[PDB]
Image: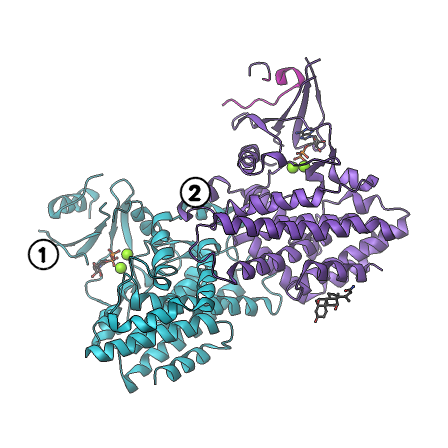
Chain colours: A purple, B cyan
Amino acid sequence: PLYETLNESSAVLAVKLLTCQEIGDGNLNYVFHIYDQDRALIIKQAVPYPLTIDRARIESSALIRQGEHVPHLVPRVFYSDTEMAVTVMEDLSHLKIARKGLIEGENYPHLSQHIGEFLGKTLFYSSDYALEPKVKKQLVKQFTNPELCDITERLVFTDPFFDHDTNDFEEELRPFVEKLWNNDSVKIEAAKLKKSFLTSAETLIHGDLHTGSIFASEHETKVIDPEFAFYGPIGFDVGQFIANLFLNALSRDGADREPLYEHVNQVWETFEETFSEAWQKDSLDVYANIDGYLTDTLSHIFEEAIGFAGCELIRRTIGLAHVADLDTIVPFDKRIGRKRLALETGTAFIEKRSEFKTITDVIELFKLLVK
Amino acid sequence: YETLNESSAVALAVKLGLTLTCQEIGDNYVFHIYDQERALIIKQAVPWPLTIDRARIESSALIRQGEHVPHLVPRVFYSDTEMAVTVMEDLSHLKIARKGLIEGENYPHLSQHIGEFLGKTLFYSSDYALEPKVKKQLVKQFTNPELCDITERLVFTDPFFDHDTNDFEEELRPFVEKLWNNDSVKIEAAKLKKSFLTSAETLIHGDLHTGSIFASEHETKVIDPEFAFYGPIGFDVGQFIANLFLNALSRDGADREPLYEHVNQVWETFEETFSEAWQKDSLDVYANIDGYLTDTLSHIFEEAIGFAGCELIRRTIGLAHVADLDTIVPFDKRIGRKRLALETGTAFIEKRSEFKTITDVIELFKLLVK
Ligand SMILES: Nc1ncnc2c1ncn2[C@@H]1O[C@H](COP(=O)(O)OP(=O)(O)O)[C@@H](O)[C@H]1O
Ligand SMILES: Nc1ncnc2c1ncn2[C@@H]1O[C@H](COP(=O)(O)OP(=O)(O)O)[C@@H](O)[C@H]1O
Ligand SMILES: [Mg+2]
Ligand SMILES: [Mg+2]
Ligand SMILES: [Mg+2]
Ligand SMILES: [Mg+2]
């Protein structure tokens, strides 16, 4: 049985393929930076408590698949190994985590075009529109992600909507939280959204595409950390990303929000064009080119995306796993206020998801609720 | 793997430990074994190629079904993947329902039974009844790529275009062509196929037509779940309802009433059974929020109807026909009823989300087939 947790030294496997430091943000994952004194490398390895190290196989394979379609939008992987639960990948230390960058006031003018093309291509080319069902059904097996899905199933879709252990919210927030716990019609909709997440095996999704999962500079965008990858609903990554743009918007004031709104607008438009051009060129489906079918498919993805976004908005505000955008808002009272707005916009997104005709409708409703 | 014969079949039976005679009776080989001094079936998959792995699916699927509705599926005594054999209870004392129904048997309990079959099989293998972690494992073991590929092609694709596998009377061409030129129906057919391709909700039977049921006045056994996989809850429901309708189309006037009552009753029973199971046995913290079960039922219903429309069309002009329609006489009356199968099927797909109840479904049908 050949699994051994790495150190700085054992990490410099690198040779078997001058200085090293562990730089990991988590505690579930080690991240080793290696630099030859002018040339650098990353070695990521899954630690076990509980949560198996099989995630490393998922993450590794998923980056590889993503690389076959959008190599410019994800780090190159040089080597990986299941038993050791290691992924050896490109260093991106010359870039900034998009969430950290956004909180600091960077605007990243190309973030939405890039993320948009990422979503369109990754989401299209792993679905039944792009692949023979026989082949696609095999990939569902290899990407079955029970333990990481269970995290999302609980935290994104469940726990925040009831009085559960894992929730974490200010007492000042209680009354609004309670208003959500008492809201049957929203909960029903969230259940529907969960059930889609549980059963809708449409494409190989990234499964955790928030702003902490992106490296960015003025001119480049890299999507990292697809360890939640499995076959899920097409609109989930779309929704989760959008929600995080809005989460940042809530941490800004007045005119400074405009870039985030423009990014929400652009990521959708670009996702739609990208998905569309790929549908046109590379669908295997005899139905693909009947006028109206693509359009209805995009309506359904769009409605799901908004519902999922609602869930992320709420879930990041009062659930186990928070975002810096909200948690570092200051002073206290302003934090609570913006946190209330995340609940309220989230709630609106879930309930009104099927009424929106365009992304602009979404932006405009948000603008209105956060005055 | 060795393909069996009358003798090696007997030997297997004796070697597993269960004055013998054997005949192959398959409509896949099916070996009937009888002790003159008690009976047994041994079904084996032959290698259209098409792997023998189906026999592993079928076998495991009868076992799962047996854990919840043992009275509605044959007992399985033994099975083996490598040999692709399933050894099961003999039901020769019963009639295939489709044959029975064409002869004029009414089977008064068929819908109650199949209703409870669907309610329980379809509930107890979904995320509502099982931990997702567990459920996702079953999805792996029931992945059915080759048998799914048959259905994806024959039920949801080929009939709707001018493809190889289609098979229909020339007299029927004009109505066929009307369907092929119908963009809006085809879009709906696409959506239904996409649900069939992606919606891994439960372990479905996958081929629950009237030729996959043994029946007598008092008993009902569902056989042949070799198409089993994780798909949409409403598909078996739809496919069964459609086959009741297909029989209706082969009857005239008053004699249709039992088929309509069956459509009505199977849905009623499916609803009540699924509902009682949800009440008792859901794991879902959402399960009891008033309105959620109802909405779920509406979506199952809506899909059921869409799938049924596909089965109506597909059985009329695709590769694999049903005796109900093909044996109608005279010719001209066949064509006429075959046109109604097209037109009711088309209605079911397009109007699927408009129907308030099963009665609305029956009533629309009755209207079109006057
Ligand atoms: N390819 C890389 N290049 C440079 N730094 C990286 C790279 N991958 C991860 N890191 C650093 O290590 C941290 C952990 O990576 P991440 O994939 O977010 O781990 P986790 O899945 O544990 O959240 C990142 O936030 C980043 O700061
Ligand atoms: N358990 C059984 N008891 C009695 N006869 C059976 C049994 N299973 C199959 N048969 C006979 O053999 C035929 C083939 O059964 P079926 O499961 O439909 O095979 P296939 O999957 O090839 O269609 C049936 O129509 C039936 O007449
Ligand atoms: Mg990360
Ligand atoms: Mg991670
Ligand atoms: Mg059969
Ligand atoms: Mg069969």
Q: With B247 as the anchor, is A254 left or right in this view?
A: right
Q: Which residues are magenta?
A: A1-14
Q: Is residue A40 above or below residue A353?
A: above
What is the chain identity of the residue bearing mark 1? Answer: B
Q: Which quadrant: the C terminus of chain B? A: bottom left
Q: Which residue is mark 1?
A: B36
Q: Amino acid at mark 1?
A: Gln
User: Magenta region, mostly helix, strand or loop?
Assistant: loop
Q: Amino acid at mark 2?
A: Gln
Q: Report the mark closest to the observer, 2 or 1.
A: 2
Few, some or many residues within 10 Å of mark 2 (<14, 14–19, 20+): some
What mark, if any, has residue B56 been given in the picture? none
Q: Nearer the viewer, residue B148 or A275?
A: A275
Residue B326 location in percent, x, y?
23, 71
Residue A176 location in percent, x, y?
79, 60
Q: Nearer the viewer, residue B76 or A113?
A: A113
- Marks 2 & 1, CB-CB < 8 Å contact: no
Q: Which quadrant: the N terminus of chain B? A: top left
Give the quarter of the image for residue B116. Answer: bottom left
Q: Regarding mark 2 in the picture, which secondary structure is present there?
A: helix
Q: Which residue is mark 2?
A: A138
Q: With A266 as the anchor, is B332 left or right in this view?
A: left
Q: Nearer the viewer, residue A152 or B317?
A: B317
